[PDB]
Length: 516
Ligand SMILES: *[C@@H]1O[C@H]1CO[C@H]1O[C@H](CO)[C@@H](O)[C@H](O)[C@H]1O
Ligand SMILES: [Ca+2]
Image 1 (spheres, rainbow, N blue to C red):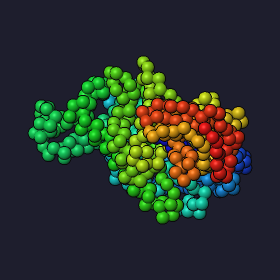
Image 2 (image 1 turned 120 degrees about the horizontal axis):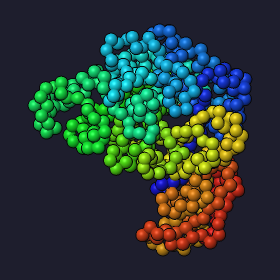
Image 3 (image 1 turned 135 degrees about the vertical axis):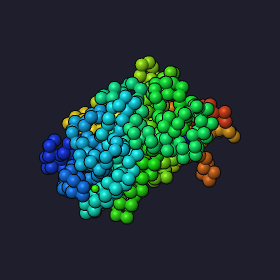
Image 4 (image 1 turned 30 degrees about the horizontal axis):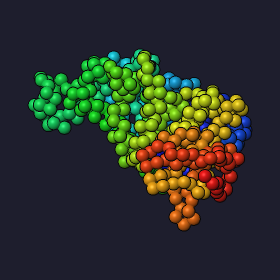
C-alpha cells in the first residue's frame, strides 16, 4: 500500500440488500439461506435501507418499525450482522433504483413557504429529500426518527455492526444537481440547487452577516450592487463555472453553498450520536457521492462536483471529522478516462479523497457505483481498497452475486478476504547505508508487483541481523512475492534471486523466511 504499508487490518466486506422488501423479492426462509451463503463467501454484514416513507408513513409519530424488526430477526437467525441505513430519502429515481418509496407526504405540509424542497437554476423542483436549509424541521423529524428507531432496534443491538445516516439524495451528502427531469444527468454539468426564495434570502442574510452592510459587500466584491435584494446566487450557472467562481463573489457563494452541507453533517451527526451512542456504541457513517464527470473539463473545471456541493473536499472532510462520522466514498471499480465529452477522472478522485481521509485520520469505506458483472472490476476495486487503506467495501447489490455463483466465486477470491498479520523475513540482504528493503507481490494486497508507490517496507532487525516486517496478508490465498533493495535515491538497486510463495497464507499468524 501507499507509504510502505500493507492492507487495513480492519478490512471487512459488506453486501447491499435489495431496495424492495424481502417478502416482495423472495421469502424469509430463502433470505436466511442466502445470508449464510454470503457469509460463506466472505461477507461480514448486509447493509439495508429502512425507508422513512415506510416507518412514519401515515403521520407525525405514527411509527411502523415492524419490517425492520422482522428483518433483523432473520439476520440474527442466519448468524449475520447488519448495517441499517436510516433512509430519510426517496427510493426510486436514482441510478439502479427499482422501487418507489417517497418520503412521508405529510412532511411537506409542515411549511407554508418553499424552505423544504429544492429549486434548480431553471426552476426544476426536487422533493426526494428535505432541503438541509430547513434545519428546524430536520432537527425535529430526524431527531424523533433516530430516537424512535434506536428504541425499536434495542433488542437487536447485537446484530448491528454500524449505522448509516442519509445526508441527502440517494443517501449521499449532496444537492440533487444531476437528474433526468432537470436535464443534468451524467455526463452533463450539474445545476445549482439554491433557487427557492428561502435559499435566496438565506444566502443574502449570510453575506450581510459576513460584511455587515451592502456598502461593505460591494467593497469586498468590487461590485456595484444597488440594493440588498440584488445579492443573489449565480444568474448563469455555466458562466459561473467558467470564470465566476474565481471572483470574491463566487468564492463566498461556494463557501455558503458547501457550508450548508457541512452544517447539515454536524447536525445529523449530533442527533445520531445522541440517539445511538449509549445503546449501540457502533460507528456511524455517512456517504460522499463520486461525481467523476466534468472533472478535468478545461472550460468548466469540476462542472459536476461544484453544483453537487463539492467545492473543497478538505473542508468537507473536516466536517465529518468534527461530526465524528466515518466516510464512505463510491466509485472504486472505475478508472480514469479524462477525455471529451465526459472528462471522467474517477480513479484520481478516489485517490485524493483517500489521501485526505487518511491524512485527517478519518475511517474510510468504499462502494461500487454500478453493478459489477466482470471480475476485472473486482480487481480494480481490490487495488484501490487494499492500497489506499480502506476499512471496508460494500458491494451493490445482493441479486448480482446471489444468483451468479461465478461472480460470487470471483468476489470471494479477490474481495471477500480476511486480513491476518504475518511476519516476513529475508536473510542476508546485500545492503549498504542508504538502502531500504521492500517486498512486492502478485495480489493487490501486495501492491501487484509495483515498486514505485505500493511496495511494502521491511526493516532491519538489529538483534538477529535480517530484514523483516509484520505484514497484513489475505488469509487462505496463494501469494507470490519477491524482496528488493531500493537505493537512497529511490531507485531499485536489486531483486531477490528466487520468487517466493505462500500457498496459501495461513489463517494463524506465523512467519515466512527466505534468503536473498
Ligand atoms: C448512492 O448509496 C449509493 C447507491 O444508492 C442506491 O443504493 C443505496 C443503498 O442501498 C440507496 O440508499 C439509494 O437510495 C440507492 O439509489
Ligand atoms: Ca416525527
